[PDB]
Amino acid sequence: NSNVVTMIRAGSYPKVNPTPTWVRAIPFEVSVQSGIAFKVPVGSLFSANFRTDSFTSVTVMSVRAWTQLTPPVNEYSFVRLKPLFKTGDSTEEFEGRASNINTRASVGYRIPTNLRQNTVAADNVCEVRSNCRQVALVISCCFN
Amino acid sequence: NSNVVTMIRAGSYPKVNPTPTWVRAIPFEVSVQSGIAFKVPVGSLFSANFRTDSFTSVTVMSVRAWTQLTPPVNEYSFVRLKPLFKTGDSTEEFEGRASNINTRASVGYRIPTNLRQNTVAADNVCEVRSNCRQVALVISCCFN
Amino acid sequence: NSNVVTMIRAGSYPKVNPTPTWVRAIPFEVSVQSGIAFKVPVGSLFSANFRTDSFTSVTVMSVRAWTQLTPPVNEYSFVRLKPLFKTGDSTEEFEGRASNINTRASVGYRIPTNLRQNTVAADNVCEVRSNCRQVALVISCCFN
Amino acid sequence: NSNVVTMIRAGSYPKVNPTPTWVRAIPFEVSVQSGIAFKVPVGSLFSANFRTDSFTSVTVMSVRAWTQLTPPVNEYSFVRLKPLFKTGDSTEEFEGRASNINTRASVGYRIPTNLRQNTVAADNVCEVRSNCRQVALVISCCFN
Amino acid sequence: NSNVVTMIRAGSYPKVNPTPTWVRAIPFEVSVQSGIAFKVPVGSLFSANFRTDSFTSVTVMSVRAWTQLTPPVNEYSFVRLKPLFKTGDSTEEFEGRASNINTRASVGYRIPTNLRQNTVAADNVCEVRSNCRQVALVISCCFN
Amino acid sequence: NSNVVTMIRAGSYPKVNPTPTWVRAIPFEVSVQSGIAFKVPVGSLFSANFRTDSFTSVTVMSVRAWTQLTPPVNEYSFVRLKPLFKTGDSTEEFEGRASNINTRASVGYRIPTNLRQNTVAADNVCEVRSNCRQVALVISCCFN
Amino acid sequence: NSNVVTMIRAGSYPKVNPTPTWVRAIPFEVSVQSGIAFKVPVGSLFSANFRTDSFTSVTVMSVRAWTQLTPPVNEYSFVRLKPLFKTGDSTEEFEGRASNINTRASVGYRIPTNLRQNTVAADNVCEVRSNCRQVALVISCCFN
RNA sequence: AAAAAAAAAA
RNA sequence: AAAAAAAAAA
RNA sequence: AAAAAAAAAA
RNA sequence: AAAAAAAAAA
RNA sequence: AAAAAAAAAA
RNA sequence: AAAAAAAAAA
RNA sequence: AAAAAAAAAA
RNA sequence: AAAAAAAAAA
RNA sequence: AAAAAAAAAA
RNA sequence: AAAAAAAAAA
RNA sequence: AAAAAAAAAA
RNA sequence: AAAAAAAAAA
RNA sequence: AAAAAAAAAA
RNA sequence: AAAAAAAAAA
Ligand SMILES: [Mg+2]
Ligand SMILES: [Mg+2]
């Protein structure tokens, strides 16, 4: 390959976009209480911590969750996800449980193409339930 | 395809990165004076206007330039690029000229793999010369 | 095949969901008045009569309608469907007519993937018009 | 694919059923005492918690069990299942044991076609034995 | 081919629709001010001038824009499009620039299937920015 | 497929037409008297009820007719069509009869390419005769 | 297949045996002391608990052992098996050790065809040694 | 990958 | 997938 | 290995 | 016959 | 399955 | 798809 | 056309 | 020779 | 293995 | 050249 | 059409 | 894609 | 013989 | 020999 700078025979000015879209896998944690569902805010996806503070909308594709702290004594960890949507919330409770007391419980869900619209900060992604005080989420989405 | 939310049989917690790299084509303009070279600052690449204010380093791959305003009376536009490098500046003057007085002049250069290291805000990319008061640049780079 | 109970070499605890989705064909009737459009409520889809009272949302895929009572004297039955959507109602009037005075008139419409979002009890599916006092609907949908 | 609503050339009124059958995997827990067998009631399968309260009968296909709490000190978890049938109870004691003290014990059994008849709330599925105070069951069945 | 009228052996009365959908490419202009974004109203798509006054909803598929008047002295034309959506506005600024001062600048964007829902008169399609006082749009859509 | 908005590399301004042609199947009814021919006016094809009020001309391709009300006592329905043309009316009487007293009679005719010219509101399509007080027409035409 | 009882064209009285042989995998536990070998009695294989109380002889094919309780503090479990035979005891000490302190240690041995003779209650199968107070055995044998 | 239940298509 | 024991079929 | 987003090449 | 949802198997 | 009209792609 | 009547073409 | 029940044949 | 139950192997 | 009667499927 | 919408044919 | 970055699948 | 000049490799 | 830099051609 | 109109057949 070349070891020096070389000329580029540029043509006309191209189509440009200073603020493009971005497909990402965003990791963040949420605090969870015993027997109570926690509504995950879409606003958590927009942050300088993820280089996404310039976005105001996002299209969520999938959600994965893991328990982030140990479970109560004698128990195995569990985590549940209930998808939420502006056009109508679901009543599914996708659940994962650990089979070793020292291991994380995990589960996830995919959003179908027909339900992949935008969401803003004030919207919620899903409800999280667990016997662990913290849950780690990894959300696959398209910032736009 | 599916019309409803479906379960994802998630496994162990994956490797994650909240602040990934980003390959981009960044468009911006610079002011140019007659007979004077303008040093293009790398700092112009880091801005909320490009969603890149969270980065402090960038690896430039190629630089393309176009005249952005009309040339002086009776003249055809021209633009020249002189690559700059922290390990030693080049003396090449890659030039493009218009063949129609109403059209932009354009030129570019590719940086070879061996010279693709990082640059920070205080560094300069290249020197620009033109008979036009403004030059539009489109820089292909890897933010990291 | 086996005539006795046999062991299952079960492994780790699986992913579970006590409240899954359900693809259905829901039959119900609506009362219709001469020259007046009847707005079909989505709420009619949630009922113990269909085993769907545990759901609060549904994604409608297609709607089919049949006249359920005889038409006025000297006439042939007819039924019209006008799709309704939260993002904007349609002005289509899909119509079917009977070709035998003693036979039902029928028609239907398919909702495209891009318009297959959720609906809740307070929403309406479509407007029904007919010269018959009752119309029988069969709605293909995904409860979630 | 289509982006708009389209007509369906519906024919005669079809055969319908407002209350269909449903093949499911039902997860629930039972409390177990040391040295005592717990009779699992079929009634636990009918609940609004599973969207099955509209059913009064079910055909069980298979039963899987996991210990749901930690075992006594110095021990490895174990779980046993004894199939029960209205025409004659079995004396099999299908057992699983953990090989790591921190892991669940698991086992299951399949019901042969010849023994797949209906069961009602007052009937029992099987007897559960364990050294753990709770057992998690996942029953594969056909609600009708 | 036949030179006279011929009989058609018609059967039963067909399914009919007096008010069908219509796929179109709608051309219209908007006034634009220096440094200010113009919100393009969906209402502009419904007009007797396009034979679309009978529609109240439309599904936009793509938007293309061209500068419609000459740019300021010494400049090249430019046009920018920022997609707007009821579920969340985008922050993309798709841009085109002219490479000849006497030529139009142009750009466009495609709406993905998952975001192709209906819009009504009060909704907005996108924001337009330009250095030209007028922009000509051609919107590909499905009236319904 | 894409889940986000994407750029379109638009070129020059295309050829456009705000008021295009439209191929349609138009359904409407006419009142018919015993032993009297009813001249079907072309004007009935132009109406807001069909989204065609912006057109003033139409090219008819084919005409189909069905009896729309029951026939007199003891009789079977019948319908006759006599094509009319500005350059010379036909004397054909294309006829259909029912073979069941409760069923519609139907018939149609195709206009040959050589006779497919435009017609305006004041023109007539055909003459209708029937023993039924109403006839339902479905006219295949090209609005222009 | 048949849904009713059907005739069997039986012939002469067959050879019969009310008390047949049985190939089994028998699970049972033994108590073990630190630094002391435990002689496993063959008599443990004959019990109503295994449905084998009607047998007085058995041919052992293989022996597998697992530690059944946790090991002493700071240690990994271990289990050793020394085969015993009426014609001459072996001096082999087949051993397994755990590689995780929370996991069972396991080992086994196969008896060659030439040493597969019968054993009665008063005979011993093998000697067991372990640092765990209990060992779980699974013996593959032929009851006769 | 096949099969069973609900749905859709053919 | 083959083999051994019980059973069934051929 | 294919696909989607950004980029580059053709 | 294929596909989508629940389940089962591989 | 082909064709005509509107649209999109190539 | 073939044939018969009128017409046209070859 | 195959299968199940009764019968017949082989 | 195949299948079902228990076991073993792969 | 085919056929006849009843049934089921196609 | 394929596809989507309206129409026509098969 | 291939490749690089982010993502998804296998 | 080939060739000429400088360089590198073979 | 291929490749890299400058040039030329296609 | 094909096609168009009327008829008949398939
Ligand atoms: Mg009848
Ligand atoms: Mg471990």
Image: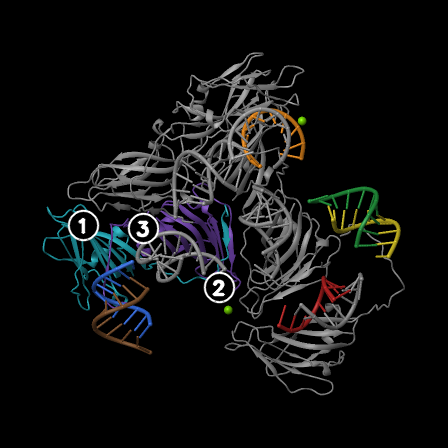
Chain colours: A purple, B cyan, N yellow, O red, P green, S brown, T blue, U orange
The answer to which quarter of the image holds residue B119 is: bottom left
Give the letter of the chain under mark 3.
A
Q: Chain of mark 1?
A: B
Front-most of residues B34 and A142 = B34
Closer to us: B126 or B80: B80
Image position of A120 (left or right of O10)? left
Q: Nearer the viewer, residue A99 or B38?
A: B38
Q: Position of residue B103 (x, y in %)?
A: 19, 47
Left or right of residue B108, residue B132 in this image: left
Q: Which mark is residue A20?
A: 3
* Marks 3 and 2, how far apart at CA: 39 Å
Instruction: Look at discs 2 and 1 and give the one toward the viewer.
Output: 1
- Image position, residue A5 (x, y; %): 23, 64
Q: Are marks 2 and 1 on the same chain?
A: no
**Could you tell whether B122 is left or right of A33 in the image?**
left
Name the foreground residue: B85 vs A8. A8
* Disc marking residue B99: 1
Classify the position of the N terminus of chain A by image quarter: bottom left
Q: In the rendered structure, which amino acid carries the disc numbered 3?
A: Pro
Q: Amino acid at mark 2?
A: Thr
- Report the Cα–Cα distance between label 2 and label 1: 69 Å
The disc labelled 1 sits on which kind of residue?
Answer: Ser
What residue appears at the point 45 percent right and 55 percent down from the top-left corner?
A64
At label 2, counting other C-alpha atoms closer than 10 Å, the crowd grade (few under 14, some 14-19, many 20 or more) is many
For residue U5, above or below residue T3? above
Which quadrant holds residue B118?
bottom left
Q: Which residue in the structure is indicated by mark 2? A: A103
Label 1 close to label 3 by CB (< 8 Å)? no
